[PDB]
Each structure stands twice: as C-alpha cells, then as structure tokens.
Amino acid sequence: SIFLRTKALLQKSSELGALPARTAEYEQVMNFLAKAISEHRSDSLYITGPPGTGKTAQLDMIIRQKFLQNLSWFELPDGRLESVAVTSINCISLGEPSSIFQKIFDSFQDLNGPTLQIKNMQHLQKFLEPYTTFVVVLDEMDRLLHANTSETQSVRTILELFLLAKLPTVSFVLIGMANSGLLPQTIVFQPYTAEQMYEIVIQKMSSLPTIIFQPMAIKFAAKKCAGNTGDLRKLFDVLRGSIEIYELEKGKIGLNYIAKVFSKFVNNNSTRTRIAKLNIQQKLILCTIIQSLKLNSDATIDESFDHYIKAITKTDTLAPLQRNEFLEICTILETCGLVSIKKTKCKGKTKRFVDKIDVDLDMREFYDEMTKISILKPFL
Amino acid sequence: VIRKFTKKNVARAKKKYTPFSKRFKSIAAIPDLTSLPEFYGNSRFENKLKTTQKHQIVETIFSKVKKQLNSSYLPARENEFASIYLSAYSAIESDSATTIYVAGTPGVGKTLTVREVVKELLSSSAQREIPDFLYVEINGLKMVKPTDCYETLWNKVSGERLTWAASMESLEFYFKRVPKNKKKTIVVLLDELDAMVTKSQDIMYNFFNWTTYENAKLIVIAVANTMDLPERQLGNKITSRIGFTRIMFTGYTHEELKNIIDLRLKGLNDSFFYVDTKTGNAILIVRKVRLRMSADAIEIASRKVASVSGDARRALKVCKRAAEIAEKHYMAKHGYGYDGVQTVHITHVMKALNETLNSHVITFMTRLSFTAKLFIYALLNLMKKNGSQEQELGDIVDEIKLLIEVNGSNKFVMEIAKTLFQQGSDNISEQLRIISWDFVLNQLLDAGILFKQTMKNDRICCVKLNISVEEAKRAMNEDETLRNL
Ligand SMILES: Nc1ncnc2c1ncn2[C@@H]1O[C@H](COP(=O)(O)OP(=O)(O)OP(=O)(O)O)[C@@H](O)[C@H]1O
Ligand SMILES: Nc1ncnc2c1ncn2[C@@H]1O[C@H](COP(=O)(O)OP(=O)(O)OP(=O)(O)O)[C@@H](O)[C@H]1O
Ligand SMILES: [Mg+2]
Ligand SMILES: [Mg+2]
C-alpha cells in the first residue's frame, strides 16, 4: 500500500554521495578528506549545528557510499585508490569517556590477532605508527567533557584526542559532530529553510510512484517547520501524523490535514476557556489564591486558606469552607489547569517541606473574566 | 594482611562483562538471532504462597460487588487506542523504528490502553499478517538502579545476564549493526519515564536514539505523567528525537466514569441471589434477594471524582468503599460472620466521599489535654500580639505564666494552678515549666501541628504553626475555659 510505504519513508529512522540540501557541506567534508588522506596528514574536523540539520545522516551517507577490520578503498580525484579504515563511534553509548581509545582499537584490530589493552592515547599513538589512513567519526563528542570536576579535567579527553589527530607520522583523522594553530576546522550545519525541506521531501518521495500529498500542503508544513531552529524531524512527525489522521478519519491529502495535525498535537488551551468552565465558588477561591500570592508570594496552602477565610468574613459571600474542602477545590483547579500545588522547602528559621501554590495563568484575561462577575470584585 | 575496614555483606550477581560486539568475529558471522534457543524469550515462585483450605468462607450479597470493582478486572479510550495501535502496526509491518509518547495524570488508563494495544498486536501477529515481535515491559519505578533497564532489556533480548555498561554497548551493537533479516522486532513499554531521568540523561538519549537507527526495528512506547516533560527536564536532542506528536490522556468525564462503573456492574446490578439466612453465604442465580446499586449514587460519585481528578481508580474505590459501608451495616444487622432488596444507596456514596474530607485536625486539637490547649492558646496570643509567625519558646513560657497569674479569679485556674506548677503536691517546689511541658511540646511536634527549629538553647528556640491559624482558633474557642477568657 502507498500509505504504509509513505509512512515508512517518513519515519525518523528512515534512510535515503550528497544530501539534497547539503551539497556545500558535502563538498567541504570531501575537500577536508582529500587534504587529509591525499597528503597523508592527520587533521581534525568539528561539525556543529542544532538538532535535525543532518550531520549524522551526511556522515553515514559519506561512509556508506564512498568507502584489520573495516578496511576499504578511498578514491581521489587523481584516482590512486588509497587504503583506509573507517569507523563511527557514538560517544554517549560508551560507559566512560576513558575507554574510547580501546574501542578505536576494538574497531580496528582483528579478532584473530593479539588484543592489547589500550589505556590512553599514548598506546593508540604507538599502535598507529606502522600504518592506510584511520578515519574515526565521533558523534556527540560534546559528551566527551565530564559533568563533574572543573575546566582542567573536563577537557582531558578531547585535548588528548586533538593531539593524537595532529602529531606527525600518523594517519589518524578526527571528525567530531556536536550539538549547539592546532584548532580543528569548523563546519556549521545550518537549520533548513522551507524550500530545502520541500526539496528533501520530494527527493525522498521520488522513489514512490504516486505522491499522496498535494505540493501546497508540503509547502505549508515546511514553512511552519522553518522557524528559528526548525528541524527535519518535526517535519517528518507532522507529515506522518497527517497520514495518521487521514486514515483514522476514513486521494491526495489536503492542506487542512496539516492544520489538523497542528491543532491536535498543540493543546491550545486558553485561560478564557478554563475560567469559563468553573463555577462561582471555584472562581472565588482562584481569586483569593491570586490575592494571597500577590501579597505573600511564598505562601502555603494553609496561609492561602487563612487569607480566604479573612476575605470571606470581610465580604460575607455565601458560606465559608473547611480547610479540606478548600484543598479539594485547589486540586479541582489543578485538574482544570489553572493552579499547581508543589512541595518545597521553606526559607525561614524552621525550614521544612510544605505544600506551595504556583499559578501558570496570565493576569490580563484572568482579570477580564473576573470583572464581568459583580459578586467577585471585592476579591480582585 | 590487616584491613583498614571490612565489607562483609557484599552480594555480587553472576553477570559477565563482555558485550555482544565481541561474541562473533564478524558482522557476517552473526546468525539469524530469531532461531537461537536463548534469544527473544526462548516463574518458579507461584507455588510458594499455596496452603490448605480447611474452612469455608462466607461471601455475602455485597462481596461480589467489592471483588468485581477492583483494579485487576476498553470503553472510553478508543481514539487513543486507535492512534497507538495504528502507529505501532505501521511500524511493525514496515520494519521501522518508532517512538510513541503518551502522557497523562494518574489512573486515566495509559498502561491499560498500551497493554490492550500490545495484546491486539500479538493476536494480529498470531494470525500471520504482521511479523512476530517481542514485547518488553520496563517500569522505571520498579528498578533499584536507573541503569538496571539496560540490564533488563538486553536480558529480554538475548537471554544473557551482563552488567549495565556491557549491556548498553550490547544494545547499541544490536540495534545499529545487526541487519533486519537476522533480527526480530521489539516493542518496549517504558512506563514512569520520569523515574528513568538522571543528571547525565544518557538512558533517555540511548533509548530514544536507538529509535532513529535504520536497522533497529525498535518501537519504544514511553508513558509520561506530564506533556511538558521533554521541554522541562530533557535536552533539545532528546526532545527532537521524541517528536512533535504526543498523545495526551485526558481525565475521564463523568459519563466515561459512569460507563466504566456500569461496565463492571453488568450482571450483578438488578440481579437475584440465593441467600442463606443461617450463615449469610449468597449464590448468583434460603431467600431470593435482589441486589441493586443505584445509578444516581454512581452518577454523584462519578461527577465528584471527574471534577477532582477524572481518575478511574478513585471512582472504583469510592464505589467499593460505599459497598463496604453497606455490607458492614448488613453484617451488623443480621449478625453474620467471617467464616428482599439489598441496595448500595446514595448515602453510602456520600459517606465514602465525605470520609476523606472531614478534617480530623480540629477534632484532634479539641480532644487534647488542658496543657496542650494552653500552649496553643499562648502561641496564638503571641501571634496576635507581635504579629510574627515564629515565636520563641521562652516567650510562650512567660505568656503561659502571665495567663495563669492574671486570670487567677477564674475557679478553674484556682483548681489547676497547684497541679500546673507543683503537681498537686507539697514537698515539690514551684516549677519553671508547667507539668508535662516537654510532653505536650513533643506531642504537638509528632502530630505535625508544630514546627520547632534545631537550637540547643530552649528559650530562644522558635516554634511555628504548621497548620492554618483559623482552624487552631476554632479548636481553641470550642474549649469552654479558653473561650471564657
Ligand atoms: N538532507 C537530508 N535528506 C534526507 N533526510 C535527511 C536529511 N537531513 C536529515 N535527514 C533525516 O533527518 C533525520 C535527522 O538527521 P540527523 O540524524 O543527521 O540529524 P543531526 O543533525 O545529526 O541531529 P542530532 O543532533 O539530533 O543528532 C534523519 O532521519 C535523517 O535521515
Ligand atoms: N477505560 C477504562 N475502562 C475500564 N477500567 C479502566 C479504564 N481506565 C482505567 N481503568 C481502571 O483503572 C485502573 C488504573 O488505570 P491505569 O493503570 O491504566 O492508569 P494510568 O493512567 O497508567 O495511571 P498511573 O499514572 O498511576 O500509572 C485500571 O487497571 C482499571 O481498573
Ligand atoms: Mg546525530
Ligand atoms: Mg501506569
């Protein structure tokens, strides 16, 4: 079926030597590779961008299409067919940052030969002398800092990797992907625009015989996904959810299904609609909570109940409530989504944990809804 | 050799350290893992809790209602069910890797809906229309360590038992490098996702980044308690990998709660039992007794529970509590033991809803001794006088002494003063604290009525009311002596 295959192509794990909107970055990475392998010179690349801009996909395409274990040939524009050994390592999925040299050894030495124990970059530096250009691609190298310690020991691993990819008479290059003169060459992957997103979607769907999308719908989805930091993953979720809603509610699918996606998965709840679903007593207790937080702003449930009792005896509207009924109406306001009760330490001379009221509603439409009720304005 | 300290209770599990990347010498050396005798799921404790039943227990007219209203036994969740089922079915049939994010408040049927989805998916796989898959359930609050999920999932996949780090590179190797034809699809339910959140956030990144791998065939269904969890606690990478689509389980309306309770009360409401009048045991079809639980009671309980939480657990528990109140009154009236119409009325439902609302704190302060009430009265007097929420204990001592020595002409004070300062006894000198001063101070500290700071000078140490001031005032002027003065 065309719907199943189209959703299969629009997954965030889907695959497709240049990416459709990454031609310039591809030529930058291949001229770095030419000046690395052809010169037999070690060098360090540092690729940076927001999420979803296609760094990992571009390096995966480069490794798959254009390339001891994992031995292969690299062809130059001259065409001398140099011998390379390429590997890619995801840094977060390692238990410690100190063992990655070992995993580089575990990516390169054959299982039939002896298995030396690599402790640091000195042992790997000894290992790479008798050789064949070694290519590593470290993904999320930014997770090679240490969250503890300070400045000195945090950079302990990346500086020793940078020295190993810069010392003479080795063939160890270092491509590092991270998220936003021995310094590495910096490439910044840019967030995509709407037209780049449209061209990527048409290129990925060009394998399909029939496009189930009107092109204006793809353009609308791409231009809504083209914000300040807009990624291709969000566009894939939006389009996949468009097929999801289209075949849950039942031809080329319309622009209206994109709006249905952006309305279904954005709960655009208004404080207008929240206040309008309450009764007079929940609105009154919301007003007393607002006034108590206005005058105290580090207030407990019990101090807010005290303020409610003082206000309700000053004004004499209906009948006063007991503390547990007050708390139950506070949880009703949690269920509606206007009041939150957390549990925090005090900052007095007797610091213990207490229940605390926070408000997540904006004042203007709150006062506008409470203005229209005449029996509530003593509490405003 | 003499040790500086000893560890004599070390319990270490039999977990190997070599990960799955070093099992075989090559990628081509890996066989089809679906044929291995240990991979993909290929209890001994259930008989330990067996005994010999030598009695005959009595199940009364309301026993079947209370047993049937439990949480162990899908009307109102059919759009969420359709969304989760269609996404997971498309991910299984195309051999894809997919994250499904589900969030909601407690008891709104998240775990029930995901479990019903995976049961229908396994039944659909049993009819050979989608490929076979392995279902893994990981609950973050059922783990000792957060990294034990690495221990759990890999043990569900391979049948090996490794330490958590080696399990993590084993799972990374399995999801990225092993081809699809040698693998089986895996559906993982991550439940209580916030419990698996650490400072490094490595488990979150790994579990949602494996769903971005081409070869993984991994479906992660993550259950959250809030929808804003990836923005509040997780980074932009994990938020990008989780995705824009997020399924929210709203709290149940009172129609939905009433439909749930009526679904559990089908076959029992408006039915007849054969009831023995000698013992009390009742049999579903000696007297023929009709059992009803009224729909107005269910609708009152459903409306209250739907406004407070929309929680199916609370609606079922309120109905079960009302039935237990009715059944307790029934056993009291007929003298039945634990070896024409019986109704769970609306009054039992109101009692069940009011028993968690009745504010025992005021009742507790009313039923205290005179010294504890005098302490609370003195503290309230100081908060009225100097307007502070924290009062020093020496000030409370001095104002208790003033309250005794000013209104002496009260007859109760003339009766109580010798007890308060000499314990009714000559040869006991006059005391600086009252009798049972530390006793009532520690008693009010145990109840949570009071907070005391941690100082070693007993006079400058501060005391604060942890309870609201108005309930302390109404408890104090309930007392006839303290409201007189
Ligand atoms: N130019 C492109 N053409 C086709 N698919 C693309 C392109 N760029 C990205 N994608 C797809 O978008 C997704 C994200 O790509 P990728 O993993 O490279 O992101 P990233 O920049 O590495 O971000 P992160 O920091 O989140 O890892 C993948 O599904 C990838 O196939
Ligand atoms: N739609 C429903 N129909 C019938 N019973 C339901 C329904 N939803 C919930 N229940 C009942 O409520 C119980 C608790 O629901 P469930 O475990 O699915 O909650 P949850 O939303 O996952 O909550 P928590 O966040 O506390 O884990 C179920 O086991 C079942 O007895
Ligand atoms: Mg990446
Ligand atoms: Mg649950």
Image: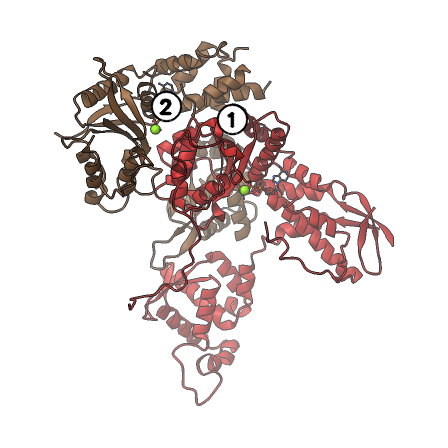
Residue nearest the viewer, comparing A308 with A133: A133
Viewport quadrant of the C terminus of chain A: top left
Say which residue label 2 marks: A231
**As drawn, B304 above or below A2:** below
Residue nearest the viewer, comparing A260 with B464: A260
Say which residue label 1 marks: B91
Q: Which hue is chain A drawn in?
A: brown
Q: Indicate the position of residue A49 as horizontal and vertical percent values.
A: 29, 26
Q: Residue at x 57, y 19 (%)?
A: A247
Query: What color scheme is it?
Result: by chain
Q: Label 2: few (<14), some or many (≥20) within 10 Å? A: many
Q: Quadrant of residue B211?
A: top left
Viewport quadrant of the N terminus of chain A: top right
Residue A227 in view? yes
Instruction: Answer with the quadrant where ligand 2 appears in the image.
Output: top right
Residue nearest the viewer, comparing A30 with A220: A30
Q: Is mark 2 within 8 Å of ligand 1?
A: yes
Task: Identify the chain drawn in red.
Answer: B
Residue nearest the viewer, comparing A42 with B453: A42
Q: Indicate the position of residue A236 as horizontal and vertical percent values.
A: 43, 21
Q: Which chain is home to disc 1?
A: B
Q: Indicate the position of residue A28 as horizontal and vertical percent values.
A: 23, 18
Mark 2 belongs to which amino acid? Asp
Residue A260 in view? no
Q: Secondary structure at mark 2?
A: loop
C-alpha span from label 1 to label 2: 22 Å
Do the dots labelled 1 and 2 sit on one chain? no
Which residue is farthest left?
Answer: A181
Would residue B100 be found to the left or right of residue A23 on screen? right
